[PDB]
Image 1 (cartoon, rainbow, N blue to C red):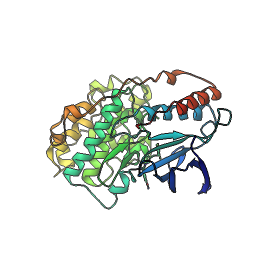
Image 2: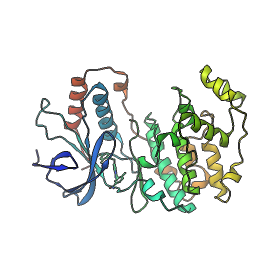
Image 3: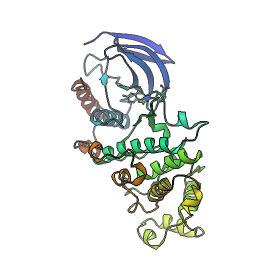
Image 4: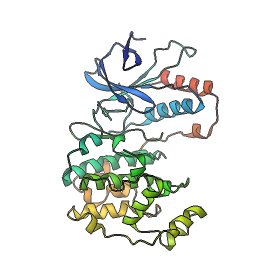
Length: 337
Ligand SMILES: Cc1ccc(C(N)=O)cc1-c1nnc2ccc(CCc3ccc(F)cc3F)cn12
């Protein structure tokens, strides 16, 4: 066991091994707080997240296990994984805190979109990396479900990693099949979000800035047109169909016109990503082979993930059970060294 030291930071207490130095708060970053630190072992900067109230309820306990399992499995240059996981607890009975550590990128995608609008070459590289990460995530039977600029960490080299897979409105980037309230979507839910991100990097504005779920659907349909016969026949929900079909029929707009002087290859990719019918939407793997990425695509360097056991997802267990399981995962952790 290494030696731990203690400090208060922004009302929050931090108990970490001495090898992590110079902790500086960087945010309240979802179900926890986050510090940038210096890892004396490697000489590299890291991000340390202290989970908030990890065993507060069955919901929190399952979430904590889910995150730790997910982060332990992700081993890909475009997805965050773990350099370290630790707890100051000496035993299971004293176990109430989890700390996770990963390479510090230092910003999200949004932290660059401000005051800037990107050239084609940078859009190609950023989206290529997103898709490269999604191919890997999707190959593990994981759907991100909340891809958005704030969930993409980006360093000064413009290298990118996807955050928070598996677990600035989310609404703005979410596929229409999940706006409508359908729980039989597929992995191309995430491809829609990529399309919204790409559009925004090219134009400099949020593609679908809706003020609620209904307005969001309305903004989406103004661009992509209202459901045709084929799609309408796949919708079970009477309320969903009745609503959609109670709207004034709207045609698909010309993407070449909406995205005027963008690379026409980018416009072609965008029209294959932002298709209403998710059965017809391009996959991450297919998108990687698209002509837009000819300068980046290498099919021998776009790997897939090892088998991911998500059987825990169907299980209804007690807090002490999720807690003990999380504990075992902390103790069995093997780093990249
Ligand atoms: C996204 C972001 C935005 C701003 C800043 C910053 N101001 O330093 C940094 C980042 C930032 N740069 N790199 C990361 C890696 C992860 C996280 C999310 C929190 C997290 C998840 C898993 C872990 F193991 C450890 C963690 F800390 C935020 N990061």
